[PDB]
Image (cartoon, coloured by chain):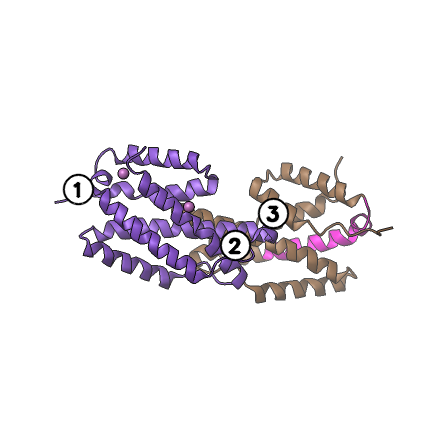
Chain colours: A purple, B brown
Amino acid sequence: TSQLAELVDAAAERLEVADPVAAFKWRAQLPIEDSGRVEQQLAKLGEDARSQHIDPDYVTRVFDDQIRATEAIEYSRFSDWKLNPASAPPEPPDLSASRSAIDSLNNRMLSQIWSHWSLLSAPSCAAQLDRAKRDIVRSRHLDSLYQRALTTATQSYCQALPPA
Amino acid sequence: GTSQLAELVDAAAERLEVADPVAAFKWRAQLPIEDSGRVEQQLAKLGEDARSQHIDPDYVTRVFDDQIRATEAIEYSRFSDWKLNPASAPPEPPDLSASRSAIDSLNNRMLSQIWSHWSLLSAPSCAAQLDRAKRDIVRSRHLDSLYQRALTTATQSYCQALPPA
Ligand SMILES: [Pb+2]
Ligand SMILES: [Pb+2]
C-alpha cells in the first residue's frame, strides 16, 4: 500500500460528493459557481492550518485544487443531464447535508496532511502519489472523468516543504 | 448514397459547433451557460420564423429546444475541462458577433430543410434515414464522442409519430 493511500482516498471521497451536490443544484436551478462561498471555505481551512502550525499557503493550494475538481464534476454531470435528463437523481440529499459532509471530510483531510507531512515534503512523494492514485483508480474502477478529477485534486500534494 | 436528411443534420451539427466559441467567451467573461429567459425568447422567434414559412411552429419549437439543450451540454463539458485545466481555455477569445451571425444563418438553413423534407420527417422511413444522415455527418465533420451524443439529442424529435393503426 502507498503511504499516501489515506490522503488520496480522502480526495476521492470528497469527489464523490460532487454528484449529489450537482443533483441538488440541477433540480433547484442553482448556479454551479459560488466564488464568494469558495473564497470563504478556503479562509477557514487556512486558519485551521495556522492553528496546527501547518503551512496555510500549501493547504489553500491543495483545497483550491480539490474544489475545482469538484466543480469540474458538477459541470460534467450538468452536461450529461442536458443530453439526457432522465439520469438526474430525483431526490438527492439537501445541499446543507452535503456541505456538512464536506466540512467533515475537510477536517479529516487536513489531519491526514499533517500526519503525512514528512512524506509529502520528501523526494519520494511523486512516486508514492502516483502509486496511491494508480491503486485507487483501479480498485474503485474510477471512470475517465474521476481519474482526471483525482489528478487535479492531488496535483499540489508534493509541493510541501520540510520543516525549518 | 446520401440521406435526404444530411443537409439538415449537417446544419444541426455545424450549429452545435458554435458551442465552442460561445463557451470560450462565457468562460473568460465569467457568465453562466444557462439562461432560461433567453432561451424562451430564442424559441419564440424561431416559432415566428416557422409561421412565416408555414412550417408547424410546435414542431420547430421541439426540435430547437433539443438543439439548444444539446448545445448547452457541449458548453458545460468545456467548462468541466477548463476547471480541470484552466490553461487550456482559449485565451482572449473573440466576441460573439461571428457566432450570432452563424446561428442566424444555420437556424434559417434548418428551417428551410424542415419544409423541404416534411414528407420524410412524417414517414416511417424517417428513423432509418436520420440514422444514415447522422452516420454520414459524424464522418464528414469528424465528430467526437461528445458531439455524437449531442447530435443524437439535437435530432431526437425530428421524426414525427406515425398513426398507431
Ligand atoms: Pb500512511
Ligand atoms: Pb465512499
Query: Is the magenta region chiefly helix, strand or loop?
Result: helix
Looking at the rendered structure, the kind of residue marked 1 is Pro
Q: Position of residue A24 (x, y in %)?
A: 50, 59
| Residues shaded magenta | B101-124
Q: Nearer the viewer, residue B100 or A144?
A: A144
The reply to whether the C-beta atoms of the residues labelled 2 and 1 are less than 8 Å apart is: no
> Residues at marks 1 and 3, common chain?
no
On-image quarter of the N terminus of chain A = top left
Whole-angstrom CA distance, mark 2 to mark 1, is 45 Å
Assign a secondary structure to mark 1: loop
Q: Give the mark, 3 or 2, whose residue is nearer the N terminus.
A: 2
Q: Is residue A6 above or below residue B23?
A: above
Q: Is residue A13 magenta?
A: no
Q: Residue at x 60, y 47 (%)?
A: B150
Residue B48 seen anywhere in this rendered image of the structure? yes
Query: Which chain letter matches label 1?
Result: A
Q: Label 1 belongs to which residue?
A: A162
Is B123 situated left or right of B146 in this image? right
B142 or B164, which is in the foreground? B164
Name above or below for residue A141 compared with residue B123.
Answer: above
Query: Percent position (x, y) of residue A37?
Result: 36, 62
Q: Residues within 10 Å of mark 2 (few under 14, many from 20)?
A: many
> Viewer-nearest of labels 1 and 3?
1
Question: Type of residue at label 3?
Answer: Ala
Query: Residue placed farthest to the left in the image?
Result: A164
Per the image, the residue denoted by label 2 is B22
**In magenta segment, residue B108:** yes
Q: Quadrant of ligand 1?
A: top left
Question: Where is the C terminus of chain A found, in terms of image quarters?
Answer: top left
